[PDB]
Image: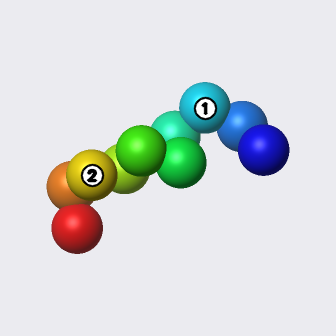
Amino acid sequence: LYRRRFVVGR
């Protein structure tokens, strides 16, 4: 994993 998994910008 990284730290952008959230990328709730979809």
Q: Position of residue 1 (x, y in %)?
A: 78, 44
User: Where does label 1 land, which residue?
Assistant: 3
Residue 2 image point, x, y percent: 72, 37
Q: Mark 2 points at which residue?
A: 8
2 to the left or right of 9:
right
**Image coordinates for residue 10, horizontal then vertical, percent:** 22, 67
Identified at 27% across, 52% down, the residue is 8
2 with respect to 10 (left or right): right
Q: Does dot 2 land on a helix, a strand or a loop?
A: loop
Is the residue marked by circle 2 packed among few (<14), some (14-19), or many (20+) residues within 10 Å? Answer: few
Q: In this view, does 9 lie above or below 2?
A: below
- In the image, residue 9 sits, relative to residue 3, either above or below, namely below
Sequence order check, earlier mark of 2 and 1: 1
- Amino acid type at circle 1 is Arg
Residue extending farthest to the right is 1
Q: How many labels does the image show?
A: 2
Measured from the top left, where is residue 7 in percent x and y? 37, 50
Q: Please, what secondary structure does the residue beneath circle 1 have?
A: loop
